[PDB]
């Protein structure tokens, strides 16, 4: 059912993509039961400068390797199913606040739960089939910082049309501006 | 440690249910592999290699433009032409024959009589799938013949009276499980 | 009764049918005469799409009449 693929919060568009999920589940028996165990937490709409909106699908963190196995195929069907759309899968991670001097101690904060760690993780999770080969931060004279991300030149054909979508969703999620470059 | 036991229990449950539905997946047959094998047999018979095209539903215009660029001469071809320009040309050809496009815009599957101007505007200004009638009108306007080869179906030819060279493309319904997808074919 | 069907490619198919034949029967005849599947063809008569589970001549479809056959081919 569409309710099983949704984890907690039901709205209309996640019910629609859950119907698309079960329609891809019953068809294509070569990938059937590879996409069955996984559920997704939430859906987010991102507006980009190109005019084609972005589906940020937030999924549980321990299930992320299961999406990593079949991500290219289900993303291709998801671009086909929804016109003028770009689909991205992210893992909804927990950011724990930095303990100040006055605050009572709540255990020890793990280093995967810091803000910079989860920002680097979702930056990696934006560009899944490519691998990041380097990063830089431009500190401009006006005080603004623009982070430049270098992508490995292999198999960039999957994501080359979606780079400004990545910039828009990263600017919305983190409040930082990034520019992608492909060293050749 | 109750937490590691809970983690192992949920992992074992996920693996067991995955194997249980994998048995039913192995029980079910795959129309995608049969359609791919039939398309490979048809491409070996026609001696032309299929070229991959991009998803999101602009595959029809992009495949038609790629097959026209492969078919027509470089002097006749224009670099300014694009998929959006092809959709605009199809909309202009639909506006050229409004009466023929009006019966084509009404669809029995959609169960409503859509407007020809609204369908042309949706084809030109949005990423919806182009119709077969609009593709045939664009092929007649560009005078390039369109050859469509479908697995398990007879080969179709449209706008063969045009002076430009024939364009070969294949629309496969079972290759993508969500629906039909068009891929350009180039002579090898 | 003999009827004519105009296709999107331009070919005119002459179908020998009856005035009490179903739209699904006409689609099966078109499949046997041209190889086009019945799930991809749409029949239209006098600017109105023919619905399945209906007989001929209910919309004044007589002999030597011209209908339209439209292939969907929605591949994207």
Image (spheres, coloured by chain):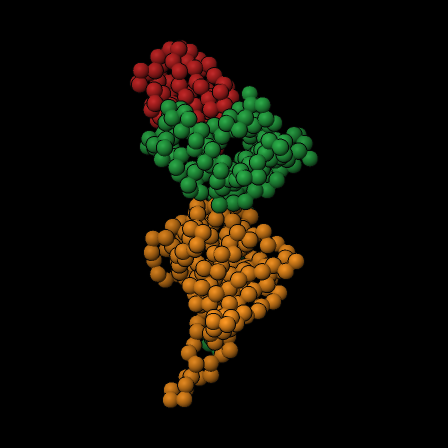
Residue at coordinates 36% horizontally, 20% vertically from top-left?
Answer: C45
Judge from the rendering whether residue C4 lies leftward or rightward of residue A10; answer left or right.
Answer: right
Question: Who's orange, chain-wise?
Answer: A
A110 and B14: which is toward the camera: A110
Question: Who's green, chain-wise?
Answer: B
Residue at coordinates 48% horizontally, 42% vertically from top-left?
Answer: B57
Q: Position of residue A95 (x, y in %)?
A: 43, 74
The answer to whether residue C53 shows anywhere in this view is no
Tally the numbered discs: 0
Question: Who's red, chain-wise?
Answer: C
B81 and B133: which is toward the camera: B81
Q: Position of residue A67 (x, y in %)?
A: 52, 58
Residue sitting at the far front: A141
Q: Position of residue A170 (x, y in %)?
A: 46, 63
In which quarter of the view is residue A171 placed? bottom left
Residue at coordinates 41% horizontally, 13% vertically from top-left?
Answer: C3
Residue at coordinates 42% horizontally, 11% vertically from top-left?
Answer: C2
Query: Looking at the figure, which quarter contains the N terminus of chain C?
Result: top left
In which quarter of the view is residue A149 placed? bottom right
Tell me: residue B61, above or below residue A87. above
A119 and B98: which is toward the camera: B98
The answer to whether residue B135 shows anywhere in this view is yes
């Amino acid at each position: 059912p569409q309710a099983k693929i949704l984890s907690q919060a039901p709205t209309e568009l996640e019910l629609q993509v859950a119907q698309a999920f079960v329609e891809l589940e019953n068809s294509s028996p070569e990938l059937k039961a590879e996409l069955r165990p996984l559920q997704f937490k939430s859906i987010r709409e991102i507006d980009v400068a190109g005019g084609k909106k972005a589906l940020a699908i937030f999924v549980p963190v321990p299930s992320l390797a299961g999406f990593h196995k079949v991500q290219t195929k289900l993303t291709r069907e998801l671009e086909k199913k929804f016109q003028d759309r770009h689909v991205i899968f992210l893992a909804e991670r927990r950011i724990l606040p930095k303990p100040s001097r006055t605050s009572r101690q709540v255990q020890k904060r793990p280093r995967s739960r810091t803000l910079t760690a989860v920002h680097d993780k979702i930056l990696e999770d934006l560009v899944f089939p490519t691998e990041i080969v380097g990063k830089r931060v431009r500190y401009l004279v006006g005080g603004n910082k623009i982070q430049k991300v270098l992508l490995d030149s292999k198999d960039v054909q999957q994501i080359d049309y979606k780079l400004e979508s990545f910039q828009a969703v990263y600017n919305k999620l983190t409040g930082k501006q990034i520019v992608f470059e492909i060293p050749s | 440690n109750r937490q590691k036991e809970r983690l192992a229990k949920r992992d074992a449950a996920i693996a067991k249910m995955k194997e249980e539905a994998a048995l039913e997946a192995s029980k079910q047959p795959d129309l995608k592999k049969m359609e791919q094998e039939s398309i490979d047999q048809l491409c070996e018979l026609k001696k032309l290699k299929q070229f991959d095209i991009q998803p999101d539903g602009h595959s029809l215009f992009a495949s038609i433009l790629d097959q026209l660029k492969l078919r027509h001469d470089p002097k006749k071809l224009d670099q300014d032409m694009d998929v959006m320009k092809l959709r605009w040309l199809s909309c202009n050809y639909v506006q050229e024959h409004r009466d023929d496009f009006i019966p084509y815009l009404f669809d029995e599957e959609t169960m409503k009589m859509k407007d020809i101007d609204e369908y042309t505007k949706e084809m030109e200004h949005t990423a919806q799938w182009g119709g077969e009638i609009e593709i045939l009108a664009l092929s007649h306007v560009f005078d390039c013949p369109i050859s469509i080869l479908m697995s398990g179906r007879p080969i179709q030819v449209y706008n063969e009276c045009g002076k430009n060279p024939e364009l070969k493309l294949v629309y496969y319904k079972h290759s993508y499980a969500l629906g039909e997808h068009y891929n350009s074919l180039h002579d090898s | 009764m003999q009827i004519f069907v105009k296709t999107l490619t331009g070919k005119t198919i002459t179908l020998e049918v009856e005035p009490s034949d179903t739209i699904e029967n006409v689609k099966a005849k078109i499949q046997d005469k041209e190889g086009i599947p019945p799930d991809q063809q749409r029949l239209i008569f006098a600017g109105k799409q023919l619905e399945d589970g209906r007989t001929l001549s209910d919309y004044n479809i007589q002999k030597e009449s011209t209908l339209h056959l439209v292939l969907r081919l929605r591949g994207g």
